[PDB]
Image (tube, rainbow over all chains, first blue to last red; front, top):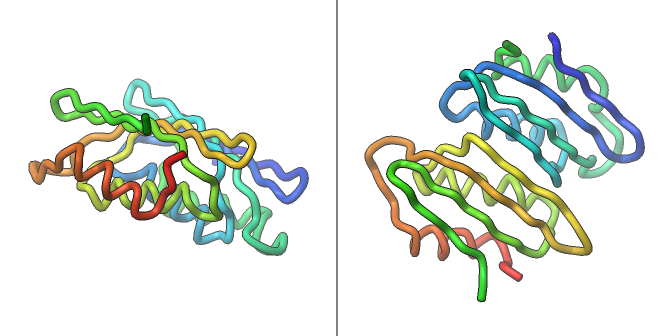
Length: 81
Length: 81
């Protein structure tokens, strides 16, 4: 819910803070890949049991599936604190 | 010289620079997961045609793997440059 996403060119930027669970980071990037997004740059940190994550990714092809579908897909596997 | 790996107790740190290919970042992390390592923190950036990556991971269970295995396993999908 309290996670933002932005688009400029062929690139998408995701900034989210969620509750940490074992393997959640790999799952989040897997959903990003399942959304036809190739993650090139990641900045992440942990603290107080929370994981702060920023992902800069680009589309593997067309701009298909880049609006709010990321939010629903990400919320399926991550609990935004 | 090449990309280095370190181990301290149950914690592992991976820092590598490799040639950028589409989808290589998730594949490297999948290999890290294939090494029974749970990645909690990832730092990655692109530049020229190279990908610089630093991964902080923990062992997924008592099935402890070894560094030389990590070096060889990572090279299967990433070209260290």
